[PDB]
């Protein structure tokens, strides 16, 4: 085969082949500074020698604390070329999360700038990366780790997820079943290196010989700045949370921007419902760019299913995540541990080449979350199958509560609220009204240009759910408060109430 993706079994070999084949092509750009594949390849080789001198060796985990930028990408390639895995540290982490990630992962060095109180003292500064810029071992194998990304810590300590070269290759080999990507694309490098969206941005581009456009620091703050850069730099592929897309749409329409240079907008991270999509579709259509909903998790290498948005999508009121990539086997599993009848909701279980090998130093959790039956991963997500094989995303599987004599599926209530045409987000929790008097309440976000009242939402909910599932109060917020991992800050919602 001529295809470098099919022919290579690790990311370093893939990169080197793509670079050597056409090394003058642009791999990465920062403003007008264009770094060719050849330049990037030599630069990262020089940085790798620097890491070898700090003792980095195959199997090491090297911390990375940098903004997404050219230096950060060189540092990733350098770490990988040493046969090591990178452990990205979000610059905005609470100090305690960064402290835990570094202790947990046993990081033996850090590239970039250490956080305040950082226990890793073996450091290669950003300046030392820049110094290698224009200079002149077997490398990793399929089964070696490429990175360790940590889950958000919703349920307990952040879980460290080691992802292998073979895992990433399997995702990259699967992408062309949904996407038409080529070497002429320009991908915006946007997300924190600590998010696995970043992994997709980087390798989506490198695996096809495409260019990674770096979002400049000056443009990091507003969607107007964001649009200005993507349009000016000829970006063709962007990756967004549905929430970011709301603000993007609003800035594009109001600013009269031309978005039609984009070929794909790819969503991940959150439910995507039609009220979030209809205004873009109204202004711009669904062809240029194509919009593609994506569902995935760190444990199964970034993305699992995709659904390209169509007119039909806009005409229904659920979040449809679509069909699994070709590497995956799937089950939808009841509470008794057995499959469910097609059409009914159960826990999504996943099998295949994209599954990680388990958590880092968590034998107990790994046995639980990665059962043999064929090895599976339990997502902790509820889904239901459509009569095509497409999945609808229902909610998290751990949101059943006991209240006032009922078991209550909060995810069901959230889903019912999100069916409303003028709602774009919602979270249902329990709060105290009078001592010993706890009730369901719902904080929600109205779509731009609307103002749905508590009375109207109550009226909508009573057509869908039994009275024991009715939120007792509604609270309109300008947006839901979020954590650094973007997970909705439930301490903050409490305070809002
Ligand atoms: N496209 C999507 N639609 C809806 N929800 C999503 C989507 N993508 C991710 N999520 C939610 O985010 C979760 C991934 O978050 P993360 O890896 O931080 O795990 P967590 O459960 O939040 O944290 P922890 O596992 O540490 O308790 C998914 O299981 C899913 O519930």
Image (cartoon, grey):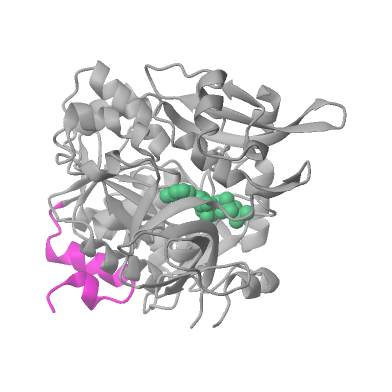
Residue 319 sits above or below residue 306 on the image: above
Q: Nearer the viewer, residue 81 or 468?
A: 468
- Residue 343 spot, x, y in % from top left: 43, 61
Count of number-bearing discs: 0
Q: Is residue 279 visible?
A: yes
- Magenta residues? 1-25
Which residue is pictured at 30% across the width and 53% down the height?
307
Q: Nearer the viewer, residue 397 or 196?
A: 397
Q: Nearer the viewer, residue 48 or 493?
A: 493
Q: Nearer the viewer, residue 80 or 130?
A: 80
Position of the C terminus, as image quadrant, is top right
Magenta residues, dominant SS class? helix
Indicate the quadrant where residue 365 lies.
bottom right
Q: Is residue 64 visible?
A: no
Q: Is residue 2 magenta?
A: yes
Position of the N terminus, as image quadrant, is bottom left
Residue 265 sits above or below residue 456 on the image: below
For this view, does 124 lie left or right of residue 389? right
Residue 92 sits above or below residue 1 on the image: above
Which residue is pictured at 20% across the width and 34% down the height?
32
- Residue 228 spot, x, y in % from top left: 24, 25
Indicate the quadrant where residue 67 lies.
top left
- Given the current orientation, which residue lies at the most extreme right position? 435
- Residue 10 spot, x, y in % from top left: 34, 73
Q: Is residue 311 magenta?
A: no
For this view, does 225 lie left or right of residue 368? left
- Residue 328 spot, x, y in % from top left: 38, 71
């Amino acid at each position: 085969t001529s295809d470098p993706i099919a022919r290579n079994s690790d990311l370093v070999s893939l990169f080197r082949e793509v670079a050597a084949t056409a090394p003058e092509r642009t791999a990465l750009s920062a403003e007008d500074d264009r770094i060719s594949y050849g330049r990037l390849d030599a630069w990262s080789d020089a940085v790798a020698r620097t890491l070898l001198a700090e003792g980095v060796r195959p199997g090491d985990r090297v911390a990375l604390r940098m903004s997404p930028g050219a230096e950060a990408i060189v540092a990733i390639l350098a770490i990988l070329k040493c046969g090591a895995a990178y452990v990205p540290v979000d610059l905005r982490n609470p100090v305690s999360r960064s402290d835990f990630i570094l202790a947990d992962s046993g990081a033996s060095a850090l590239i970039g700038e250490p956080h305040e109180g950082c226990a890793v003292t073996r450091v290669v500064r950003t300046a030392a990366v820049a110094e290698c810029k224009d200079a002149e071992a077997p490398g990793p194998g399929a089964e070696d780790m490429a990175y360790v990304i940590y889950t958000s810590g919703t349920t307990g300590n952040p879980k460290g997820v080691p992802v292998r070269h073979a895992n990433v290759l399997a995702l990259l080999a699967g992408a062309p079943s949904v996407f038409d990507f080529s070497g002429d694309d320009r991908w915006l490098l946007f997300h924190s290196l600590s998010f696995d969206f970043s992994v997709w941005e980087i390798w989506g581009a490198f695996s096809t010989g495409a260019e990674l456009v770096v979002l400049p620091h000056w443009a990091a703050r507003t969607p107007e700045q964001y649009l200005a850069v993507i349009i000016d730099r000829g970006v063709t592929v962007i990756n967004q949370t549905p929430t970011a897309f709301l603000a993007l749409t609003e800035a594009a329409v109001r600013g009269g921007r031309d978005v039609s240079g984009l070929r794909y907008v790819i969503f991940g991270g959150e439910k995507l419902t039609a009220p979030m999509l209809r205004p873009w579709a109204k202004a711009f259509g669904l062809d240029r760019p194509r919009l593609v909903n994506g569902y995935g998790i760190t444990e199964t290498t970034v993305f699992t299913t995709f659904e390209e948005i169509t007119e039909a999508y806009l005409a229904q009121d659920a979040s449809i995540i679509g069909r699994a990539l070709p590497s995956f086997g799937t089950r939808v599993v009841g509470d008794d541990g057995r499959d469910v009848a097609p059409g009914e909701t159960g826990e999504l279980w996943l099998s295949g080449a994209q599954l990680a090998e388990g958590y880092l130093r968590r034998p107990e959790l790994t046995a639980e979350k990665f059962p043999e039956v064929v090895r599976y991963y339990r997502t902790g997500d509820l889904v239901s199958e459509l009569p095509d094989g497409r999945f609808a995303y229902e909610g998290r599987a751990d949101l059943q509560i006991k209240l006032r004599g009922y078991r209550i599926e909060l995810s069901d209530i959230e889903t019912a609220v999100r069916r409303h045409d003028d709602v774009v987000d919602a979270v249902v929790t329990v709060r105290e009204f009078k001592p010993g008097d706890l009730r369901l309440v719902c904080a929600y976000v109205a779509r731009e240009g609307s103002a749905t009242t508590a009375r109207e939402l109550r009226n909508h909910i009573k057509t869908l759910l039994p009275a024991y599932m009715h939120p007792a109060r509604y609270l309109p917020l300008p947006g839901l408060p979020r954590t650094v991992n973007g997970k909705v800050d439930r301490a903050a919602v409490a305070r809002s109430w």
